[PDB]
Image (tube, rainbow over all chains, first blue to last red):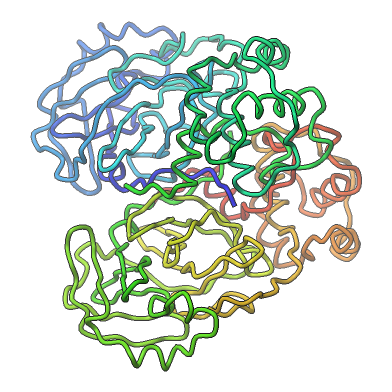
Length: 304
Length: 304
């Protein structure tokens, strides 16, 4: 029993609204008296091929923005563009506004997605920002404006707003200041994502979770060095492990009595030899979308 | 992109409370003016070995029940035992009570769990009632009273309350009327779960999801009959497929142009020959915790 757990989504559900600008409807995020949504709400299908957002936004007035929050309708009394997000000032501050921050997460970190369609939640799931700054999400047409978040104590840290599906079926989006993660632009054009790599520090976290849960078959006698492990990681397109990464795995090393460079030697053997048809935590592949904090949080029963 | 999506958990988060009876604290569910919790809240560690619940409950008064809902404290003004659940009547009806039903689900059906500790949500995840009526949950000590649910439109259908971890590391619990799923009792004693089987109709649903998502490598020319497929299912400890199951897969057969008995022939080949180190929806094992409704719901973008 060790599952991909999402944060409780209630505090975010109270902030989701529908944003319409002419034909185009998508999702928005209502905090205080501001509604944050992808700036392409102002594009026709045709416009998306090569949009001049400054020129399109100039053609728009407040009354070209229909924001609904359930049956309630909301009065747009202001618009500005910040990077790739539109901020619609509305007359009424959201009474369900949680305590919140906006944060820009690092590649390899995880967050919960509340997938929405026409401003209504469909579901909640946990996922990782890939090292190439894409997400392998589950999103359909109309999911744009869905948000990713983390919760600490009583504060929602919003880290992602969903914009687009790449022609390769992976997902790209912004921070809540409208800055893309990775090299992407909000235009319907072919765009290259980097080579993706496996998040090595997260695989090691998940192997510690496996030990805590009684799966120990993969443990071996040996150790190694960051320098030697990283030669094998490079060969299997694993991210290089740094001392920063060893430092973050410390508490899991302490709980299990398995030194970080010792678990790395077990990972090396798994990469070189495969799993020989056995499973770890009932997976036949190595899982990289659990961080060391995620493992500690889950294994120690942290609440919000 | 096809993930295990949980229901949005907000409407359930507003109903979770802490229930203390002397030393013992666990979680409870506050609907209208009734708080539902596992009847073993009235047991000491020692009592759990061989409890006489009628005799223990008689020793208890309302003032031996401390219910907290955040900082708010709640006044217990009544107690009754229904099967394996305690109903604590409280003076104040929950202002956050959603529209709700109590339902008894069938083996193979899925639901969302809101994992709680001291009446505070930790996380939300999707899981299946196994054919042997256990759940392979992610629960720690103090998770008892956590609930499982489904959401349709605006109504929460509560189907599970978590009671216990079996000495084998799987989970058992009740419906919200306090009736165990499966042969289990709320006593700290060794208890046999059946042989578990794989939920065949859910594997077929997930193979349809795979096709919809562009994974088609596993499709073959052949067909079969329920009678012939079921001979192979019996050998691989798969649940027998009935016409009821074929009827439920109809819409997915229609969407993909792959007849149900035709997908069954592909499953047969996968069971007999393995996956030869390839993946389906990035899994190297066959997934059985997505129902046909779950696949349709996700692939068609159903909201609440």
